[PDB]
Image (cartoon, rainbow over all chains, first blue to last red; front, top):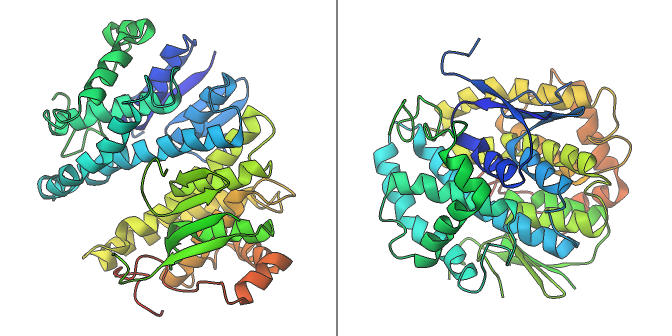
Length: 206
Length: 206
């Protein structure tokens, strides 16, 4: 049975957890707690260990899961489209993490929220003509986008008010039966968003 | 003929330029200058346009180039190994870019250089038993690592003194005949490393 190790936070691994649940894959987690500051080629968290594949790097892990289930794309062109959406989502998600620990969070937050709409608009447009980011079926960047939306909603609860197709998208991901079940389950990690020491999305509760 | 658009800087695209030269691929560049602040799904620089594939996101572009030439890996496991090295190199490269524009660069530089050795050591070890990062043949993360080494050498010319296998690796990449030729050519962009407004690796010369 595959093992996924990470902090007991959403953080970098939450989209991977959503994907695993979507696929109904069986896995156990090694969940590291706040005080728990006390082979694998590139030691880090997260790590993914299955049947003697030992992986670090969050993107390598999610892509591996996707790949194993033939979700990365059929041809070089389709694969690049997936990697493009992937990078575009990460600009949002890292955009948050990059300031979340800063003394100046509240100030930096202004500049991030200022640029967020232009970032969201590309996904908005992508979704005017498509059910999920890559058309009719779910791909891993759908879960990365879900996680990003969930996060920026804590930062600014109105950030999606100008974006109805993103709102419906996020409800749609939540309506997927495997995902609905996971979100209501005891395995779901609601909080924190970032490491507990974060100025934003840190702490033991919202 | 494929078009690669980016700033006329090393920046995010330098490893892609090295890969293209390695493959002896023919391409033209759209090079945007400092004052030149005045379809494509996710508008950005860099962009890669070939035969009606219109790509943004630097990683999507390099991976696409690799993919087209069957360099991304044979099986899900090999592909994940490549994506792992990729992410590991990016921790170094983004590590630089993340502070390069900061008022506090000189201070932040201390903490980055402090953590760099532990990051370099994993590649050092990888290279005690392998010619290139993935064994006998070159893969795209080899060029990403090359670019990262070139950059941190401007930051700290002694950072590789404890790492002989990295030193020999960087000489080895340079000895590849296509790369040696490119480095001495008129297409080679030596400087700047970051956007010209950067506190580190910016400006018109070293």
